[PDB]
Image 1: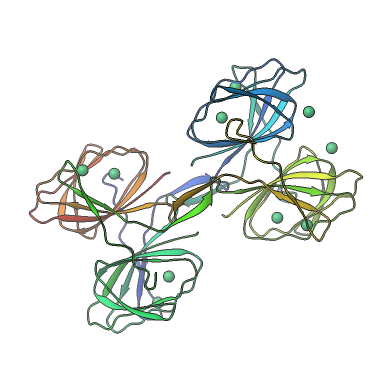
Image 2: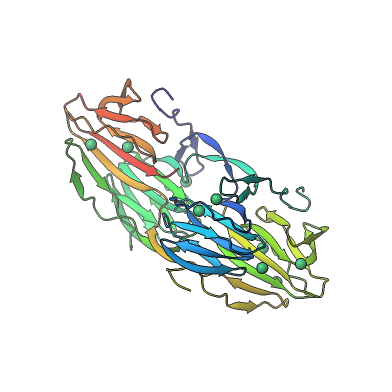
Amino acid sequence: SVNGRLPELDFENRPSGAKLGIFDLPKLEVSVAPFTLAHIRVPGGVTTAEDHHEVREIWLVQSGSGILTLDGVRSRVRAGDTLYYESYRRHQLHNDGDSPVEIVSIWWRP
Amino acid sequence: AHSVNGRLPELDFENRPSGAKLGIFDLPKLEVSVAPFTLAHIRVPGGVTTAEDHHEVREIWLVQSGSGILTLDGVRSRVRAGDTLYYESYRRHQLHNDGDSPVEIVSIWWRP
Amino acid sequence: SVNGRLPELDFENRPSGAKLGIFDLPKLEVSVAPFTLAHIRVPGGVTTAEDHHEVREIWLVQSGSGILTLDGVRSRVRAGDTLYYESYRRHQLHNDGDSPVEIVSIWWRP
Amino acid sequence: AHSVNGRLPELDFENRPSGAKLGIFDLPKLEVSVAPFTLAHIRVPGGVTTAEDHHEVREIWLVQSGSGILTLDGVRSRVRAGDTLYYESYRRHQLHNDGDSPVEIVSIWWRP
Ligand SMILES: [Cl-]
Ligand SMILES: [Cl-]
Ligand SMILES: [Cl-]
Ligand SMILES: [Cl-]
Ligand SMILES: [Cl-]
Ligand SMILES: [Cl-]
Ligand SMILES: [Zn+2]
Ligand SMILES: [Zn+2]
Ligand SMILES: [Zn+2]
Ligand SMILES: [Zn+2]
């Protein structure tokens, strides 16, 4: 740790006569999934903060309808639309309906 | 919610300054290596023939010392120090050290 | 390819005096996502085939209701439930309603 | 569906023998390495000091030949052939070869 060395190899003697040593690297706690799964609820009248991030992102719009602004281009989305945002694309959703927009969001590091 | 139904817990929603709400699904956790590969050293003494390998992980061999005869999908070829090999998934490989010196290999394996 | 050798290294001379050679590995076409995203529609009366696979899997049940059998244990799921299936758990869904069960499925290699 | 709305195409559903229907979302594709890491050789001639590195990728150094003085987050230490080092993300590292021989390193880097 202080100088970052890995422990010395413990070699296994294999039946063939070969020797095999596996490097013992640090462990860490991770999610079973290589992505983050979330739900976004946008009430009526809400505009989300303009998002931009290196993680890639998918939106599965489940309910409601809104004006997506994607890199300056406005378009309407609704329940049943599915969207993919490449790294760093600027996205923002304005819900101009009475009922909430419900979104399943998935994001992951490229 | 439990392992018997596989059901994930109810979401806890956070309020964002915009008025939107964000809930993150709480998935199960796991202890894994800091590395998405396995790093290994293989030493093949003089006269040894490794076991014929046939596995799903991709594999890189950085041959460091010595020399021997790689058999790769039935094709015989010589490999020596400074060679670097890449074995696509499920390719049969087997090394016979016909020298007197050990062949030393840094091996990297990972799931496609 | 015939003997699997990588091409010889092309070393770059760095301003420090060090040399850096990067190994040129084979390329391949992949999805931008490290998982597969799908939709499963189970009509009324349908029972899905008993699934089992090494990939991990999440179901986001969007609509309808059914009897999940998970490793021999029966339970009811509905729209709004979200499920995680570890590698090799046996899952199967019977839709005993009039209307279809709609599921967003995500699977990925552990 | 296009890049201007980011919208994915409508699903094409397949009938399964059970009566269920399966549609797979068609996501965009990309050319990547067969390996989830970058594999490199670093050669530090006698007297050379590498640039101080400070980056997000994790890094493994398999020192093969020679010897020098690693500086790791301001701590000076000697590294020699046969040493294997692991640099967690954003750890400052810099190698000074105070010998006459080159230090040769197999370096592996990857995104946490
Ligand atoms: Cl927001
Ligand atoms: Cl709606
Ligand atoms: Cl063996
Ligand atoms: Cl089925
Ligand atoms: Cl429903
Ligand atoms: Cl440098
Ligand atoms: Zn976002
Ligand atoms: Zn092997
Ligand atoms: Zn399944
Ligand atoms: Zn570095």
